[PDB]
Length: 95
Image 1 (cartoon, rainbow, N blue to C red):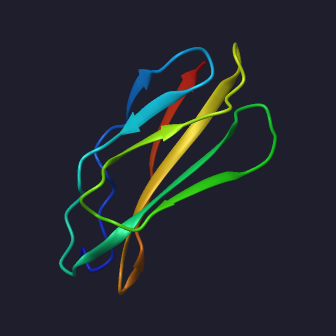
Image 2 (cartoon, helix red, strand yellow):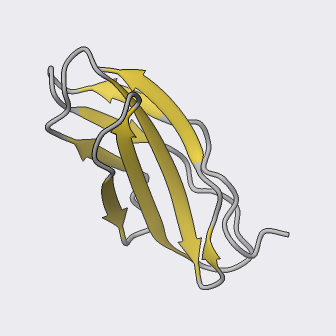
């Protein structure tokens, strides 16, 4: 039922200046060892797909840079096990 990781907990956003933030979550349940996370983010109204891969399940935060002021973004965080990638936790924010 949770061989691939469950969804992470709700995303917490912390502003770090005008073009950066910290995105944070908590480690999701999994019946298999967690291998890491992906953080995918994209302008709400369209743009390039950005991805940060975090190969350590103990790191549940990351600093995201070069964001556009006054623009809205969709962040999607997933965790990986040997069984595959789990469902995303989605959170949105305006910079």
